[PDB]
Protein backbone atom coordinates (compact mmCIF):
# COMPACT_ATOMS: atom_id res chain seq x y z
CA UNK A 1 0.00 0.00 0.00
CA UNK A 2 0.78 3.70 -0.16
CA UNK A 3 -0.80 4.91 3.07
CA UNK A 4 -1.66 8.60 3.06
CA UNK A 5 0.41 10.38 5.73
CA UNK A 6 -2.41 11.30 8.12
CA UNK A 7 -4.33 8.00 8.34
CA UNK A 8 -4.91 5.77 11.40
CA UNK A 9 -4.23 2.08 10.75
CA UNK A 10 -6.30 -0.40 12.77
CA UNK A 11 -4.36 -2.82 14.98
CA UNK A 12 -5.60 -6.03 13.36
CA UNK A 13 -4.64 -6.07 9.66
CA UNK A 14 -6.95 -8.82 8.47
CA UNK A 15 -9.42 -8.76 5.56
CA UNK A 16 -12.28 -11.00 4.47
CA UNK A 17 -13.21 -10.97 0.77
CA UNK A 18 -15.95 -12.93 -1.03
CA UNK A 19 -14.63 -14.58 -4.23
CA UNK A 20 -17.85 -15.70 -5.87
CA UNK A 21 -17.02 -19.39 -6.25
CA UNK A 22 -14.57 -22.17 -5.39
CA UNK A 23 -11.59 -21.73 -7.77
CA UNK A 24 -10.69 -24.18 -10.53
CA UNK A 25 -7.12 -24.39 -9.24
CA UNK A 26 -4.28 -22.46 -7.72
CA UNK A 27 -1.89 -23.48 -10.55
CA UNK A 28 -1.57 -20.40 -12.82
CA UNK A 29 -1.41 -22.56 -16.00
CA UNK A 30 -4.74 -24.24 -15.26
CA UNK A 31 -6.97 -21.22 -14.56
CA UNK A 32 -9.21 -18.94 -16.69
CA UNK A 33 -11.68 -17.00 -14.51
CA UNK A 34 -12.07 -13.93 -12.40
CA UNK A 35 -12.23 -15.89 -9.10
CA UNK A 36 -9.04 -17.81 -10.02
CA UNK A 37 -7.24 -14.60 -11.02
CA UNK A 38 -8.19 -12.67 -7.84
CA UNK A 39 -6.29 -15.15 -5.63
CA UNK A 40 -3.45 -15.73 -8.22
CA UNK A 41 -2.39 -12.04 -8.16
CA UNK A 42 -1.77 -12.23 -4.37
CA UNK A 43 0.27 -15.42 -4.70
CA UNK A 44 2.26 -15.21 -8.01
CA UNK A 45 3.97 -12.20 -9.57
CA UNK A 46 5.05 -12.01 -13.21
CA UNK A 47 7.20 -9.52 -15.14
CA UNK A 48 4.80 -6.56 -14.91
CA UNK A 49 1.91 -5.85 -12.48
CA UNK A 50 -0.88 -3.24 -12.59
CA UNK A 51 -0.60 -0.11 -10.40
CA UNK A 52 -3.64 1.21 -8.46
CA UNK A 53 -4.87 2.98 -11.59
CA UNK A 54 -4.66 -0.14 -13.78
CA UNK A 55 -1.56 0.91 -15.76
CA UNK A 56 1.24 -1.57 -16.42
CA UNK A 57 4.18 -1.29 -14.06
CA UNK A 58 7.39 -2.97 -13.02
CA UNK A 59 6.77 -6.27 -11.24
CA UNK A 60 9.63 -8.80 -11.12
CA UNK A 61 11.15 -6.82 -14.04
CA UNK A 62 12.37 -3.38 -12.98
CA UNK A 63 12.64 -2.05 -16.50
CA UNK A 64 12.31 -3.43 -20.02
CA UNK A 65 13.01 -2.48 -23.66
CA UNK A 66 12.40 -3.58 -27.23
CA UNK A 67 13.97 -3.46 -30.67
CA UNK A 68 11.40 -3.06 -33.49
CA UNK A 69 8.59 -4.15 -31.10
CA UNK A 70 9.87 -7.71 -31.87
CA UNK A 71 12.65 -8.47 -29.33
CA UNK A 72 11.65 -7.62 -25.71
CA UNK A 73 14.28 -7.54 -22.97
CA UNK A 74 13.31 -7.66 -19.32
CA UNK A 75 15.72 -6.54 -16.61
CA UNK A 76 14.74 -8.46 -13.51
CA UNK A 77 15.44 -7.11 -10.00
CA UNK A 78 18.17 -8.74 -7.90
CA UNK A 79 16.08 -8.97 -4.71
CA UNK A 80 13.23 -11.01 -6.29
CA UNK A 81 12.67 -14.24 -4.32
CA UNK A 82 10.31 -17.10 -3.67
CA UNK A 83 8.54 -17.84 -0.39
CA UNK A 84 11.22 -20.42 0.58
CA UNK A 85 14.12 -17.97 0.26
CA UNK A 86 15.36 -19.07 -3.15
CA UNK A 87 15.73 -16.38 -5.80
CA UNK A 88 13.54 -15.53 -8.74
CA UNK A 89 15.59 -15.64 -11.96
CA UNK A 90 15.03 -15.50 -15.71
CA UNK A 91 15.33 -19.34 -15.78
CA UNK A 92 12.04 -19.58 -13.86
CA UNK A 93 10.32 -17.59 -16.66
CA UNK A 94 11.89 -19.67 -19.47
CA UNK A 95 10.60 -22.88 -17.74
CA UNK A 96 7.15 -21.42 -16.90
CA UNK A 97 6.33 -20.16 -20.42
CA UNK A 98 7.52 -23.48 -21.85
CA UNK A 99 5.22 -25.44 -19.54
CA UNK A 100 2.29 -23.09 -20.48
CA UNK A 101 2.89 -23.78 -24.20
CA UNK A 102 3.31 -27.53 -23.84
CA UNK A 103 0.23 -29.41 -25.02
CA UNK A 104 0.60 -31.89 -22.12
CA UNK A 105 -0.22 -29.09 -19.66
CA UNK A 106 -3.54 -28.56 -21.56
CA UNK A 107 -3.92 -24.95 -20.29
CA UNK A 108 -7.17 -23.15 -21.30
CA UNK A 109 -4.80 -20.16 -21.84
CA UNK A 110 -2.14 -21.95 -23.93
CA UNK A 111 -3.17 -19.55 -26.81
CA UNK A 112 -2.16 -16.53 -24.63
CA UNK A 113 1.38 -17.11 -26.08
CA UNK A 114 -0.13 -17.08 -29.61
CA UNK A 115 -1.77 -13.69 -28.73
CA UNK A 116 1.72 -12.29 -27.81
CA UNK A 117 3.03 -14.03 -31.06
CA UNK A 118 6.10 -15.68 -29.50
CA UNK A 119 8.36 -17.40 -32.04
CA UNK A 120 7.45 -21.02 -32.82
CA UNK A 121 4.30 -21.09 -30.67
CA UNK A 122 2.04 -22.36 -33.45
CA UNK A 123 4.25 -25.39 -34.12
CA UNK A 124 4.60 -26.14 -30.42
CA UNK A 125 0.83 -26.08 -29.83
CA UNK A 126 0.36 -28.39 -32.85
CA UNK A 127 3.03 -30.86 -31.51
CA UNK A 128 5.43 -30.34 -34.46
CA UNK A 129 8.18 -28.84 -32.33
CA UNK A 130 8.91 -29.23 -28.62
CA UNK A 131 8.35 -26.47 -26.04
CA UNK A 132 12.09 -25.96 -25.58
CA UNK A 133 12.08 -24.29 -29.04
CA UNK A 134 9.83 -21.45 -27.78
CA UNK A 135 11.33 -17.99 -28.55
CA UNK A 136 12.28 -17.16 -24.93
CA UNK A 137 15.69 -17.07 -23.31
CA UNK A 138 17.60 -16.36 -20.15
CA UNK A 139 20.57 -14.23 -21.28
CA UNK A 140 21.68 -14.23 -17.63
CA UNK A 141 20.09 -14.78 -14.21
CA UNK A 142 18.38 -11.41 -14.31
CA UNK A 143 17.87 -10.98 -18.05
CA UNK A 144 14.89 -12.50 -19.82
CA UNK A 145 14.66 -12.04 -23.59
CA UNK A 146 11.57 -12.60 -25.76
CA UNK A 147 11.49 -13.04 -29.55
CA UNK A 148 8.15 -12.44 -31.38
CA UNK A 149 7.54 -13.53 -35.01
CA UNK A 150 5.67 -10.25 -35.72
CA UNK A 151 5.84 -6.72 -34.29
CA UNK A 152 3.48 -6.41 -31.26
CA UNK A 153 3.52 -2.84 -29.86
CA UNK A 154 1.21 -3.73 -26.99
CA UNK A 155 3.16 -6.92 -26.03
CA UNK A 156 4.05 -5.48 -22.60
CA UNK A 157 0.37 -4.95 -21.65
CA UNK A 158 -0.28 -8.78 -21.80
CA UNK A 159 2.26 -9.47 -19.05
CA UNK A 160 0.14 -8.63 -16.00
CA UNK A 161 -2.01 -11.74 -16.71
CA UNK A 162 -1.67 -14.65 -14.29
CA UNK A 163 -1.00 -17.31 -17.03
CA UNK A 164 2.42 -15.74 -17.65
CA UNK A 165 3.28 -15.73 -13.91
CA UNK A 166 6.19 -17.96 -12.94
CA UNK A 167 5.71 -21.29 -11.21
CA UNK A 168 8.44 -23.01 -9.08
CA UNK A 169 10.10 -25.85 -11.07
CA UNK A 170 11.20 -27.77 -7.92
CA UNK A 171 7.70 -28.10 -6.51
CA UNK A 172 5.88 -28.83 -9.77
CA UNK A 173 8.37 -31.60 -10.64
CA UNK A 174 8.35 -33.11 -7.15
CA UNK A 175 4.64 -33.00 -6.26
CA UNK A 176 3.04 -32.77 -9.71
CA UNK A 177 -0.67 -32.06 -9.21
CA UNK A 178 -0.17 -31.81 -5.42
CA UNK A 179 2.26 -28.89 -5.81
CA UNK A 180 -0.49 -26.41 -4.91
CA UNK A 181 -1.45 -27.97 -1.55
CA UNK A 182 -0.38 -25.64 1.29
CA UNK A 183 2.22 -28.19 2.41
CA UNK A 184 4.10 -28.02 -0.91
CA UNK A 185 3.45 -24.59 -2.44
CA UNK A 186 6.09 -21.99 -3.15
CA UNK A 187 4.96 -18.47 -4.19
CA UNK A 188 6.68 -15.13 -5.17
CA UNK A 189 3.86 -12.67 -4.61
CA UNK A 190 3.09 -10.64 -1.49
CA UNK A 191 1.23 -13.59 0.11
CA UNK A 192 1.68 -17.31 0.56
CA UNK A 193 -0.94 -20.02 1.13
CA UNK A 194 -1.87 -20.72 4.78
CA UNK A 195 -5.02 -22.88 4.44
CA UNK A 196 -7.38 -24.07 1.72
CA UNK A 197 -10.65 -25.68 2.81
CA UNK A 198 -12.61 -26.82 -0.28
CA UNK A 199 -15.91 -24.93 -0.40
CA UNK A 200 -15.19 -23.07 2.82
CA UNK A 201 -12.19 -20.79 2.69
CA UNK A 202 -8.73 -20.03 1.30
CA UNK A 203 -6.57 -18.20 3.84
CA UNK A 204 -3.39 -16.31 2.89
CA UNK A 205 -0.58 -14.81 5.03
CA UNK A 206 2.03 -12.09 4.37
CA UNK A 207 5.14 -13.29 2.53
CA UNK A 208 8.30 -12.14 4.34
CA UNK A 209 10.42 -12.83 1.26
CA UNK A 210 8.38 -10.66 -1.13
CA UNK A 211 10.72 -7.96 -2.44
CA UNK A 212 8.24 -5.20 -1.58
CA UNK A 213 7.18 -6.63 1.80
CA UNK A 214 8.04 -3.30 3.50
CA UNK A 215 4.94 -1.67 1.95
CA UNK A 216 2.49 -4.52 2.46
CA UNK A 217 -0.03 -3.69 5.22
CA UNK A 218 -2.51 -6.63 5.45
CA UNK A 219 -1.14 -9.71 7.18
CA UNK A 220 -4.00 -12.13 6.60
CA UNK A 221 -6.56 -12.24 3.78
CA UNK A 222 -9.42 -14.78 3.63
CA UNK A 223 -11.09 -15.66 0.31
CA UNK A 224 -14.64 -16.98 0.53
CA UNK A 225 -16.39 -18.93 -2.28
CA UNK A 226 -20.08 -17.92 -1.89
CA UNK A 227 -21.95 -18.00 -5.25
CA UNK A 228 -25.22 -16.75 -3.80
CA UNK A 229 -25.16 -12.95 -4.13
CA UNK A 230 -27.89 -12.64 -1.44
CA UNK A 231 -25.98 -14.71 1.14
CA UNK A 232 -22.85 -12.64 0.37
CA UNK A 233 -24.55 -9.29 0.84
CA UNK A 234 -26.18 -10.55 4.08
CA UNK A 235 -22.85 -11.72 5.46
CA UNK A 236 -21.46 -8.30 4.65
CA UNK A 237 -24.36 -6.17 5.94
CA UNK A 238 -24.24 -8.25 9.15
CA UNK A 239 -20.49 -7.60 9.64
CA UNK A 240 -18.69 -10.86 8.66
CA UNK A 241 -17.33 -9.85 5.17
CA UNK A 242 -15.42 -6.66 4.18
CA UNK A 243 -15.45 -6.65 0.35
CA UNK A 244 -18.23 -8.42 -1.49
CA UNK A 245 -17.64 -10.26 -4.73
CA UNK A 246 -18.62 -8.04 -7.68
CA UNK A 247 -21.98 -9.57 -8.73
CA UNK A 248 -24.93 -7.76 -6.98
CA UNK A 249 -28.30 -9.51 -6.45
CA UNK A 250 -31.32 -7.90 -8.09
CA UNK A 251 -33.41 -8.40 -4.93
CA UNK A 252 -31.58 -5.94 -2.65
CA UNK A 253 -29.52 -3.64 -4.89
CA UNK A 254 -32.30 -0.99 -4.76
CA UNK A 255 -32.53 -0.76 -0.97
CA UNK A 256 -28.76 -0.70 -0.18
CA UNK A 257 -27.90 2.32 -2.43
CA UNK A 258 -29.50 4.74 0.04
CA UNK A 259 -29.62 2.43 3.06
CA UNK A 260 -25.79 2.51 2.69
CA UNK A 261 -24.78 4.75 -0.26
CA UNK A 262 -21.10 5.07 0.70
CA UNK A 263 -20.51 1.32 0.76
CA UNK A 264 -21.86 0.82 -2.79
CA UNK A 265 -19.08 1.13 -5.36
CA UNK A 266 -20.20 1.29 -8.99
CA UNK A 267 -17.47 1.77 -11.62
CA UNK A 268 -16.75 1.11 -15.31
CA UNK A 269 -15.60 -2.45 -16.17
CA UNK A 270 -14.27 -3.98 -19.41
CA UNK A 271 -16.55 -7.06 -19.43
CA UNK A 272 -19.47 -8.13 -21.66
CA UNK A 273 -22.38 -10.39 -20.54
CA UNK A 274 -23.65 -12.54 -23.41
CA UNK A 275 -25.39 -15.79 -24.27
CA UNK A 276 -22.78 -18.04 -25.96
CA UNK A 277 -24.13 -20.27 -28.75
CA UNK A 278 -22.36 -23.55 -29.48
CA UNK A 279 -21.82 -22.78 -33.18
CA UNK A 280 -21.04 -26.38 -34.25
CA UNK A 281 -24.13 -28.13 -32.80
CA UNK A 282 -27.26 -28.40 -35.00
CA UNK A 283 -29.52 -26.47 -35.33
CA UNK A 284 -27.32 -23.62 -33.97
CA UNK A 285 -24.83 -24.14 -36.86
CA UNK A 286 -27.46 -22.38 -39.04
CA UNK A 287 -26.95 -18.61 -39.11
CA UNK A 288 -30.73 -17.94 -39.32
CA UNK A 289 -31.47 -19.61 -36.00
CA UNK A 290 -28.58 -17.74 -34.26
CA UNK A 291 -29.70 -14.43 -35.80
CA UNK A 292 -33.26 -14.89 -34.59
CA UNK A 293 -32.22 -15.47 -30.97
CA UNK A 294 -30.00 -12.36 -31.07
CA UNK A 295 -32.75 -10.11 -32.50
CA UNK A 296 -35.60 -11.34 -30.28
CA UNK A 297 -33.82 -10.73 -26.95
CA UNK A 298 -35.15 -7.41 -25.54
CA UNK A 299 -32.05 -5.74 -24.04
CA UNK A 300 -34.08 -2.76 -22.84
CA UNK A 301 -36.19 -4.98 -20.55
CA UNK A 302 -33.29 -7.08 -19.27
CA UNK A 303 -30.96 -4.17 -18.59
CA UNK A 304 -33.17 -1.16 -17.80
CA UNK A 305 -36.13 -3.00 -16.14
CA UNK A 306 -35.09 -6.41 -14.75
CA UNK A 307 -31.46 -5.71 -13.70
CA UNK A 308 -31.42 -1.95 -13.34
CA UNK A 309 -27.86 -1.43 -12.02
CA UNK A 310 -26.42 0.86 -14.71
CA UNK A 311 -25.16 -1.69 -17.27
CA UNK A 312 -25.35 -0.59 -20.96
CA UNK A 313 -27.26 -2.55 -23.67
CA UNK A 314 -24.75 -4.36 -25.85
CA UNK A 315 -24.49 -4.82 -29.62
CA UNK A 316 -20.96 -6.23 -29.80
CA UNK A 317 -18.39 -8.45 -28.04
CA UNK A 318 -15.65 -5.92 -27.44
CA UNK A 319 -16.92 -3.11 -25.13
CA UNK A 320 -17.01 0.18 -27.07
CA UNK A 321 -14.99 2.07 -24.40
CA UNK A 322 -12.06 -0.38 -24.70
CA UNK A 323 -8.81 1.43 -25.59
CA UNK A 324 -8.46 1.62 -29.39
CA UNK A 325 -12.02 0.47 -30.19
CA UNK A 326 -14.04 2.50 -32.76
CA UNK A 327 -17.12 0.33 -33.32
CA UNK A 328 -20.06 0.83 -35.69
CA UNK A 329 -23.56 0.28 -34.19
CA UNK A 330 -25.26 -2.33 -36.42
CA UNK A 331 -28.51 -1.64 -38.34
CA UNK A 332 -30.55 -4.10 -36.29
CA UNK A 333 -29.74 -2.35 -33.02
CA UNK A 334 -31.31 0.90 -34.33
CA UNK A 335 -34.65 -0.70 -35.19
CA UNK A 336 -37.64 -0.91 -32.82
CA UNK A 337 -38.02 -4.12 -30.81
CA UNK A 338 -41.21 -4.95 -32.72
CA UNK A 339 -39.36 -4.94 -36.10
CA UNK A 340 -36.57 -7.12 -34.64
CA UNK A 341 -39.22 -9.64 -33.45
CA UNK A 342 -40.96 -9.85 -36.88
CA UNK A 343 -37.57 -10.25 -38.61
CA UNK A 344 -36.60 -12.92 -36.03
CA UNK A 345 -39.88 -14.80 -36.53
CA UNK A 346 -39.44 -14.89 -40.31
CA UNK A 347 -35.90 -16.27 -39.97
CA UNK A 348 -37.01 -19.10 -37.68
CA UNK A 349 -39.94 -20.04 -39.95
CA UNK A 350 -37.56 -20.21 -42.97
CA UNK A 351 -35.33 -22.55 -40.89
CA UNK A 352 -38.30 -24.90 -40.25
CA UNK A 353 -39.35 -23.82 -36.75
CA UNK A 354 -42.87 -22.64 -35.99
CA UNK A 355 -45.52 -22.55 -33.27
CA UNK A 356 -46.76 -26.19 -33.16
CA UNK A 357 -43.20 -27.54 -33.86
CA UNK A 358 -40.90 -25.13 -32.09
CA UNK A 359 -37.23 -24.85 -31.34
CA UNK A 360 -36.53 -26.22 -27.84
CA UNK A 361 -33.06 -26.09 -26.22
CA UNK A 362 -31.11 -26.12 -22.97
CA UNK A 363 -29.80 -22.90 -21.46
CA UNK A 364 -26.76 -23.55 -19.22
CA UNK A 365 -25.78 -21.11 -16.46
CA UNK A 366 -23.43 -21.23 -13.49
CA UNK A 367 -25.04 -21.33 -10.04
CA UNK A 368 -25.91 -17.84 -8.85
CA UNK A 369 -28.92 -15.82 -7.69
CA UNK A 370 -28.27 -13.22 -10.40
CA UNK A 371 -27.76 -15.60 -13.37
CA UNK A 372 -30.84 -17.71 -12.48
CA UNK A 373 -33.06 -14.60 -12.27
CA UNK A 374 -31.78 -13.32 -15.65
CA UNK A 375 -32.04 -16.78 -17.20
CA UNK A 376 -35.73 -16.97 -16.17
CA UNK A 377 -36.46 -13.51 -17.60
CA UNK A 378 -34.66 -14.21 -20.92
CA UNK A 379 -36.46 -17.56 -21.35
CA UNK A 380 -39.86 -15.89 -20.99
CA UNK A 381 -38.93 -13.09 -23.46
CA UNK A 382 -37.81 -15.66 -26.04
CA UNK A 383 -40.96 -17.72 -25.42
CA UNK A 384 -43.07 -14.56 -25.91
CA UNK A 385 -41.25 -13.06 -28.93
CA UNK A 386 -40.42 -16.31 -30.81
CA UNK A 387 -42.37 -19.21 -29.32
CA UNK A 388 -39.19 -21.07 -28.34
CA UNK A 389 -39.09 -23.36 -25.29
CA UNK A 390 -35.92 -23.34 -23.15
CA UNK A 391 -35.02 -25.77 -20.37
CA UNK A 392 -32.81 -24.12 -17.70
CA UNK A 393 -29.77 -26.01 -16.42
CA UNK A 394 -27.30 -25.02 -13.70
CA UNK A 395 -23.75 -26.23 -12.95
CA UNK A 396 -21.14 -25.24 -10.35
CA UNK A 397 -18.45 -22.87 -11.73
CA UNK A 398 -15.65 -25.35 -12.54
CA UNK A 399 -17.95 -27.91 -14.16
CA UNK A 400 -19.67 -25.12 -16.13
CA UNK A 401 -16.34 -23.88 -17.61
CA UNK A 402 -15.34 -27.46 -18.51
CA UNK A 403 -18.66 -28.22 -20.27
CA UNK A 404 -18.23 -25.12 -22.45
CA UNK A 405 -14.70 -26.23 -23.46
CA UNK A 406 -16.00 -29.73 -24.26
CA UNK A 407 -18.94 -28.39 -26.35
CA UNK A 408 -21.62 -30.50 -24.51
CA UNK A 409 -24.09 -27.63 -24.41
CA UNK A 410 -26.55 -25.76 -26.62
CA UNK A 411 -26.64 -22.18 -25.31
CA UNK A 412 -24.80 -20.87 -22.26
CA UNK A 413 -24.76 -17.71 -20.17
CA UNK A 414 -21.20 -16.28 -20.32
CA UNK A 415 -19.13 -13.29 -19.34
CA UNK A 416 -15.70 -12.24 -20.64
CA UNK A 417 -13.53 -9.57 -19.09
CA UNK A 418 -10.44 -8.07 -20.70
CA UNK A 419 -7.00 -9.40 -19.76
CA UNK A 420 -5.26 -6.30 -21.15
CA UNK A 421 -6.87 -3.06 -22.44
CA UNK A 422 -6.85 -3.39 -26.27
CA UNK A 423 -9.54 -4.95 -28.52
CA UNK A 424 -7.61 -8.20 -29.30
CA UNK A 425 -8.04 -9.27 -25.60
CA UNK A 426 -11.67 -9.98 -26.68
CA UNK A 427 -11.28 -10.66 -30.43
CA UNK A 428 -8.40 -13.23 -30.21
CA UNK A 429 -10.77 -15.53 -28.23
CA UNK A 430 -12.88 -15.97 -31.40
CA UNK A 431 -9.93 -17.16 -33.58
CA UNK A 432 -10.61 -20.65 -34.95
CA UNK A 433 -7.76 -22.34 -33.07
CA UNK A 434 -7.88 -20.44 -29.81
CA UNK A 435 -7.92 -22.41 -26.55
CA UNK A 436 -10.39 -19.76 -25.17
CA UNK A 437 -12.85 -20.24 -28.09
CA UNK A 438 -15.82 -21.78 -26.12
CA UNK A 439 -18.29 -20.57 -28.77
CA UNK A 440 -16.60 -23.13 -31.10
CA UNK A 441 -16.84 -20.41 -33.80
CA UNK A 442 -14.58 -21.00 -36.81
CA UNK A 443 -14.37 -18.37 -39.56
CA UNK A 444 -11.40 -18.04 -41.95
CA UNK A 445 -12.58 -14.52 -42.86
CA UNK A 446 -12.44 -13.51 -39.18
CA UNK A 447 -9.03 -15.13 -38.61
CA UNK A 448 -7.53 -13.26 -41.59
CA UNK A 449 -8.82 -9.88 -40.38
CA UNK A 450 -7.13 -10.39 -37.05
CA UNK A 451 -3.95 -11.80 -38.66
CA UNK A 452 -3.74 -8.61 -40.78
CA UNK A 453 -3.82 -6.32 -37.71
CA UNK A 454 -0.18 -7.13 -36.95
CA UNK A 455 0.87 -6.37 -40.56
CA UNK A 456 -0.54 -2.85 -40.96
CA UNK A 457 1.75 0.14 -40.34
CA UNK A 458 -0.26 2.18 -37.84
CA UNK A 459 -2.92 2.27 -35.12
CA UNK A 460 -5.57 3.92 -37.31
CA UNK A 461 -5.56 1.04 -39.83
CA UNK A 462 -5.60 -1.44 -36.93
CA UNK A 463 -8.77 0.18 -35.42
CA UNK A 464 -10.56 -0.02 -38.75
CA UNK A 465 -9.72 -3.75 -38.95
CA UNK A 466 -11.01 -4.31 -35.37
CA UNK A 467 -14.27 -2.62 -36.39
CA UNK A 468 -14.60 -4.92 -39.42
CA UNK A 469 -13.84 -8.02 -37.30
CA UNK A 470 -16.72 -7.12 -34.93
CA UNK A 471 -18.95 -6.68 -38.02
CA UNK A 472 -17.91 -10.17 -39.20
CA UNK A 473 -18.82 -11.71 -35.78
CA UNK A 474 -22.13 -9.82 -35.83
CA UNK A 475 -23.07 -10.84 -39.34
CA UNK A 476 -22.43 -14.52 -38.42
CA UNK A 477 -24.35 -14.07 -35.04
CA UNK A 478 -21.68 -16.06 -33.26
CA UNK A 479 -23.04 -14.94 -29.87
CA UNK A 480 -25.98 -12.94 -28.42
CA UNK A 481 -24.57 -9.76 -26.73
CA UNK A 482 -26.66 -8.62 -23.71
CA UNK A 483 -24.85 -5.87 -21.78
CA UNK A 484 -21.50 -4.20 -21.02
CA UNK A 485 -20.91 -4.65 -17.25
CA UNK A 486 -20.53 -2.13 -14.50
CA UNK A 487 -18.20 -3.12 -11.68
CA UNK A 488 -20.56 -3.28 -8.67
CA UNK A 489 -19.80 -4.31 -5.12
CA UNK A 490 -19.88 -3.42 -1.43
CA UNK A 491 -16.69 -1.97 0.14
CA UNK A 492 -16.67 -1.35 3.93
CA UNK A 493 -15.71 2.12 5.18
CA UNK A 494 -12.48 1.00 6.82
CA UNK A 495 -11.07 -0.83 3.79
CA UNK A 496 -8.55 1.63 2.28
CA UNK A 497 -6.91 1.73 -1.16
CA UNK A 498 -9.77 0.66 -3.49
CA UNK A 499 -9.98 3.56 -5.97
CA UNK A 500 -12.06 1.63 -8.51
CA UNK A 501 -10.60 3.49 -11.50
CA UNK A 502 -8.98 0.31 -12.91
CA UNK A 503 -11.40 -0.88 -15.62
CA UNK A 504 -9.84 -4.39 -15.38
CA UNK A 505 -10.30 -4.52 -11.59
CA UNK A 506 -6.81 -6.03 -11.22
CA UNK A 507 -6.77 -5.63 -7.37
CA UNK A 508 -3.80 -6.56 -5.21
CA UNK A 509 -4.42 -7.10 -1.45
CA UNK A 510 -0.92 -5.67 -0.82
CA UNK A 511 -2.15 -2.28 -2.07
CA UNK A 512 -4.94 -2.15 0.53
CA UNK A 513 -4.97 -1.36 4.28
CA UNK A 514 -7.43 -1.44 7.19
CA UNK A 515 -8.31 1.82 8.96
CA UNK A 516 -8.94 2.21 12.68
CA UNK A 517 -12.67 1.99 13.40
Image: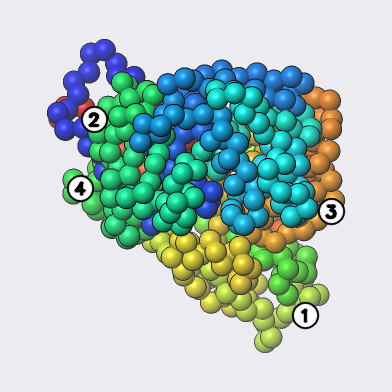
Query: From this viewpoint, which residue is outermost toward the bottom?
Result: 356
Snapshot quadrant of residue 157: top right
Q: Nearer the viewer, residue 234 or 352?
A: 234
Please say if the residues under marks 4 and 2 sit with CB atoms less than 8 Å apart: no
Q: Nearer the viewer, mark 3 or mark 1?
A: 3
Q: Hey, which quadrant is residue 189 in on the image?
A: top left
| Residue that mark 2 sits on | 514
List the single residue furthest toward the top. 5
**Observer able to see residue 61:** yes
Q: 217 or 358: nearer the eye?
A: 217
In the rendering, at what x and y percent does residue 153 appear?
71, 26
Vertical relation: 499 (above or below) 100: above
Q: Residues within 10 Å of mark 3 (few under 14, many from 20)?
A: few
Q: Nearer the viewer, mark 1 or mark 4?
A: 4
Write down the residue under mark 4: 240
Measure the C-alpha gap from mark 3 to mark 4: 52 Å
Work out how far the residue at label 3 is from the one at label 1, CA to CA, in angstroms: 28 Å
Dot 3 and dot 2 residues touching (CB under 8 Å):
no
Q: Eyeballing the image, is 336 above or below 222?
A: below
Disc 3 vs disc 4: Cβ atoms closer than 8 Å? no
Q: Which residue is tagged 1?
A: 352
Secondary structure of the residue carrying numbered label 4: loop
Indicate left or right for 304 with 228 as reference.
right
Of circles 2 and 1, the one toward us is 2
Task: Provide the residue designation for mark 3.
Answer: 444
What kind of element bears circle 3? helix
Label 1 residue SS: loop
Q: Earlier in the sequence, mark 4 or mark 2?
A: 4
Judge the density around disc 2: few (<14), some (14-19), many (≥20) Cα neighbours within 10 Å. many
Q: Nearer the viewer, residue 137 or 512?
A: 137
Rendered view: 388 above or below 202: below
Amino acid sequence: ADVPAGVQLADKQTLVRNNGSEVQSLDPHKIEGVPESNVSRDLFEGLLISDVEGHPSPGVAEKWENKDFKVWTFHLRENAKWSDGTPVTAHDFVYSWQRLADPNTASPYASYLQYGHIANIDDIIAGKKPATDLGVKALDDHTFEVTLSEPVPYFYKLLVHPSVSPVPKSAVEKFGDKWTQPANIVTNGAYKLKNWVVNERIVLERNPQYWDNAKTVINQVTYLPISSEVTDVNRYRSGEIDMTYNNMPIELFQKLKKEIPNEVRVDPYLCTYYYEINNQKAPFNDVRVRTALKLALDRDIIVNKVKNQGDLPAYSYTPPYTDGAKLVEPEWFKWSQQKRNEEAKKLLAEAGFTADKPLTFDLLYNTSDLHKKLAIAVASIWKKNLGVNVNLENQEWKTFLDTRHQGTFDVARAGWCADYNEPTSFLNTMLSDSSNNTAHYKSPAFDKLIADTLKVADDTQRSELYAKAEQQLDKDSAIVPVYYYVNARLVKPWVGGYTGKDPLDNIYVKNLYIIKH
